[PDB]
Length: 275
Image (cartoon, rainbow, N blue to C red; front, top):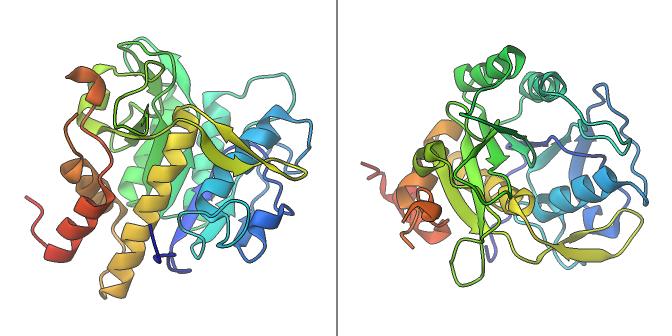
């Protein structure tokens, strides 16, 4: 993403595990933690602290640190929903985090998680929270899941969501990335192999999966919103989704709507000629 860094007027919420905001890669970031019901304190031995710190660093890691982020100048809203405790969290817990983020003025909500479903069915609370995003023009960007099946996770499969699958550095979809029917319309592939991110308590690690491709797309979406602001436009998250989907590049079914095409998305935004 070269020299583009984002605009502090664009708010990106990370709904994940705890984030170690004391990691050196976040020095200079504008991050606000919004306690919801899950613990907010990061632990170096926590699986969800690891997950959330890594995901957050992909977007908000600062230039010249150990993890350069995609949109280091955007405002980050950290909304911990995943827990280091053994217990899973529910679709209701997700819905609560989504409402927290919408109410805090998020433009983009990154959810690097979800639940496997038969048909993209979801609990009513989660359906309602996603509807709230759609009604307020807040873009939910969500992980497709790693099962590798003709199947769907929620919230990735839900209306107006941007689902994100994983590709390798040659642009081929990973085996371990889901490709259910709804993703052909609203899913894109982003880099998901050996993605650099921060570790709670210090250091970095390269991780693979749709959870790590997801924040790359959220970051790019944030840069596109930032460009809208620069142009004197009202930020329009659902338009940014449309631009990302329209500009996605061909690779059959495991390509989803296509591969993330950042230069193409910017060219379409700049020309005004989306069709």
